[PDB]
Amino acid sequence: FTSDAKDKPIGCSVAISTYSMLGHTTKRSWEAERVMEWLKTQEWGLMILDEVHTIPAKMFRRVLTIVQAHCKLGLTATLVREDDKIVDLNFLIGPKLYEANWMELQNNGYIAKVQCAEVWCPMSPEFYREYVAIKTKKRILLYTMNPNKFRACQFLIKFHERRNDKIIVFADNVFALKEYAIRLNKPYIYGPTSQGERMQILQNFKHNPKINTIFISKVGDTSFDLPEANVLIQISSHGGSRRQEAQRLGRVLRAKKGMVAEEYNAFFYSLVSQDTQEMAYSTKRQRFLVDQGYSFKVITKLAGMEEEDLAFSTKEEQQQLLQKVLAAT
Amino acid sequence: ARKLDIDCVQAITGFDFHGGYSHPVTDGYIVCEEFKDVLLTAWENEQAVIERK
DNA sequence: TGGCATAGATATCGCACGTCTATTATCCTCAGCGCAATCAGCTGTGACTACCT
DNA sequence: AGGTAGTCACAGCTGATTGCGCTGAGGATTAGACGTGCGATATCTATGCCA
Image (cartoon, rainbow over all chains, first blue to last red; front, top):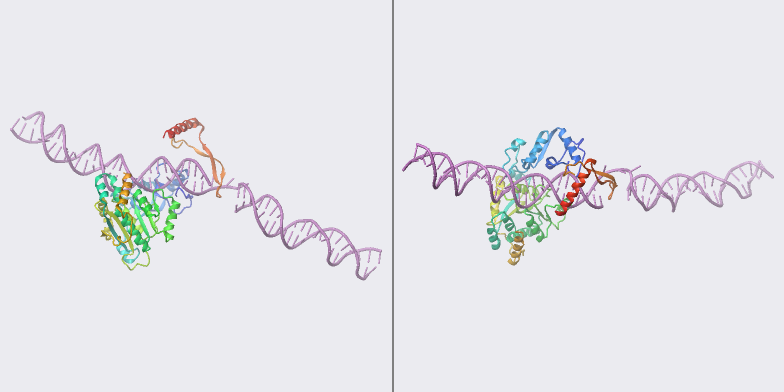
């Protein structure tokens, strides 16, 4: 029951739809109205809800009232909504039935044994002075565009490509993602995300060994399917969504054969700018992953960056980058 | 019409098939005769508004 | 002498081999909705001072 | 002259704000016909066979 692939609801034993298709307060298409009438008339023995953490929103909560079903079951990767709207969910659906131990599943090899790391990036003096000068929400651009952070990301990408690793780089900021991907000349996916070209890029990453570095915007959380990867580099995050980026880490890194015996077969890096507010976010966020026993070893400096030539070696380039960033306020 | 909540349908004229599928072809909107001139006035107003916008 | 088979001469209809435009329901785009950390104003609480006793 | 209510100066709570996601309307987008080529096939009659 989507707006693109339309099918007759009659005789449909299992009907699959989205919350928005049921949450449309505005007038729908005429056929959509008929299908909604059919759904409302029909009583469901089973209802299944995915990504339960999005349910507590008011529009999606109204969907439960809209639909009449006997058995409702919810599945997700996390259950800590940052707006603490979870107590109501205990009766929106019901009690938490089960929660597998992440470390135990790692031991059994059902999922990859992740190697987590937080990488601190020094701030350029001009960038840091500007960051201190600004006091409002506009500070996001400056530290997300740290030349040292760019150099660290470039070095990590080079090292893992030389290791022939699946590199997926997240960047919630639209502008930062564009600049990073373009300068590194790698595919980028953001708001537009033409679905055909989106799947084209995904298949290029999956099949072409020449291209194994995909830059993805915030849409990488739940807006599409993530092919199994091994190296996940997170540059910018929402700013305290302890469950969102933890879920992103869980979805990105999957079980891979070959290195099951080793305790570190999946590699995750979180780039954080030193002396910025971003640090306060990271410690705030990865707390959830700490609840699952995951550890994050601080890597102030990366070995090998000296010999390999990287971008922004001269500060004269870096001040031009500062020009570009400040141009967008 | 939907902005003014006026029931308006397409006017199925024929069939066109570019890649092998007979998509129905419509020429304008069928509306009730009662709101014909009101709809014309609304269209004129919205045309002027979108011009200045 | 005369009945008519037997093949020379010939199209003749059927099976098979070329094009052609449509006896009927697609593919991207912009406007309309939604979600999560600041920031600021409504309201509550303490410090300072007026008035009845 | 004496103390607690009115008034002003600051604090918690919550709604508005600003990045960002999703549908609905709207404008773009080779299968019987009609023949022939080839191939199997009915088709008509010379004329000399010997009774």
